[PDB]
Length: 155
Length: 259
Ligand SMILES: Cc1ccccc1[C@H](CC(=O)O)NC(=O)c1cc(OC[C@H](O)C(C)(C)C)n(-c2ccccc2F)n1
Ligand SMILES: *[C@@H]1O[C@H](CO)[C@@H](O[C@@H]2O[C@H](CO)[C@@H](O)[C@H](O)[C@H]2NC(C)=O)[C@H](O)[C@H]1NC(C)=O
Ligand SMILES: *[C@@H]1O[C@H](CO)[C@@H](O[C@@H]2O[C@H](CO)[C@@H](O)[C@H](O)[C@H]2NC(C)=O)[C@H](O)[C@H]1NC(C)=O
Image (cartoon, rainbow over all chains, first blue to last red; front, side, top):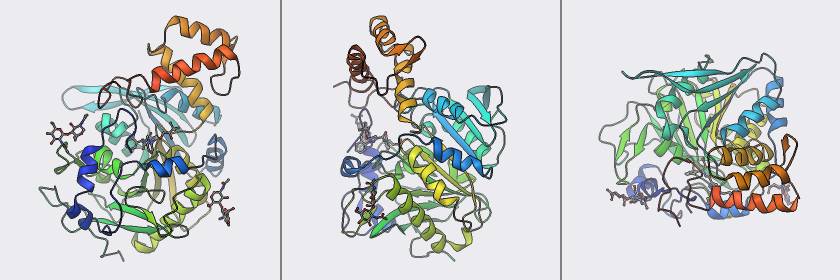
C-alpha cells in the first residue's frame, strides 16, 4: 500500500480514526483508508506515452497559462525530463533561462530555482526539493503558486 | 447555494477553529463512481478567489496526501492525531478542491466495486466530477478555474484540461503540474543521465552505457534493443529504485532503512 522509502502512517492513522471519518461525512460501510490503492494501480491501463499533443491542443487557444514545476532532487519524475519536454513543444516568445528568487525571513533573498519561459508556458525547478515540492520547500512552493495564479513572472 | 450537508463542523486534532468554510463529501463521476472530495475555501476573499483542483498521482494515490502532508490548510503531525495550521497553505489565496481519484482511491468508491480503469475513463470521470462540483457549489461557476496535480497527474491534468477547454461554462484559466510524468521517453533518458551525474553510477557502467546505448551524441535508454545496453539499464534501475536510495528525494533518508 506504501510506495518505497515513504512513510504515510501519520495521515493513515488520522484518516482511519472513526470520529475523523464522521467529521468528513464518510459512510461507515466503506473499507479502511489507504494512501495508495494497490488494486487500482495493478488494474490501471496506461494509454498515453506523451502529453505533447494535449499541451499543443491547450496552447493553440492561447487562453491558458501552463506551468511545469519540478523538484531538482527527485528521481521518479526528474526535472530534466520535464525541461526537455517543455523545450520540445517549440513555443514562441522564448525567454532566456533565469533564476527565480524567494525572500527567506532575515536570511535574505535566495535562488529558489530556475525558470525557462515561453508564450503561455513556463518550466520551473525547485532547488533542493524532491518529488513533493510543497513538503520539502513550502515557502518556495507558495511563492511559485501565488505568481502562477496571479499570472505574474516567476523571477 | 452550497451543500450544507457536506460542511465539516468540528474537525478532530485542530486546537483552533478555521476562519474558512470547509466541505467533505462526494462528487458523481461516470457510471456508479462516487469520488470523495475535501474542499477548502480561501482564507482571503473566498467568493472572488480562484477554484483550484488538486490531484495526486500513483495511479491509485490519494489527493488527501496533498492536503495533510503537502499544501493543505493544516498538516498532520507524527502522532497521527494533531493537526497544525500551515502558514504556506495554498488555500490562503485560493478555494482548493482535493479530489480522491479515480474510484477506489482512499474514501472514493463505486457501487459495483470495479476499480479497473484507464487514462480516457479517468479524465471523463474527473470531468463529470467537476460538473457535479459546480452543481453543488453554483456560486463558484464564474470563478477562475485552475487544474493542478503531481506525478501521474502529469497525465491526469492535461487530458482533463482538454475536456474542460471544450466546456464554455467552466472558466478555465490554467494548469500546473508538479514533478509530472509528461513523456516516458524523456523521463527514462534524462534519469540515466541524472543517475550518473549525481554519482550513483560509476565510470565503468557509464562508459558501457555511452558505447552501447548511444550513437555519437544521441542516447537511447527508453526502447533500445542493444544487448550490453539492456544489461546496463537493468543495473541502473536496481541502483536508482531498489538499492536503498529514496527515489522521491535523493538526499533524504529511506523510511524504514535500506532493505
Ligand atoms: C510517493 C507518494 C506518497 C504519497 C502519496 C502519493 C505519492 C506518489 C504520487 C504523487 O506524488 O502524487 N506516488 C507514486 O509515485 C506511486 C507510484 C506508484 O506505482 C509505481 C508505478 O506504477 C510503477 C510500476 C511504474 C513503478 N505508486 C503506487 C500506487 C499504488 C500502490 C503502490 C504504489 F507504490 N505510487
Ligand atoms: C513512520 O511514521 C510514524 C508516524 O509519524 C512514526 O511513528 C511515530 O514515532 C514517533 C517517535 O517514536 C512518535 O512520537 C509518534 O507518536 C509515532 N506515531 C505513530 C502514529 O505511531 C514511525 O516511527 C515511522 N516509522 C518509520 C520506520 O520511519
Ligand atoms: C477505457 O475504459 C473505458 C471504460 O471502461 C472503455 O470503454 C468501454 O468499453 C466497454 C467494453 O468494450 C464497452 O462496453 C463500453 O461501452 C465502453 N464505454 C465507452 C464510454 O466507450 C475503453 O474501451 C477503455 N479503453 C481501452 C483502450 O482499454
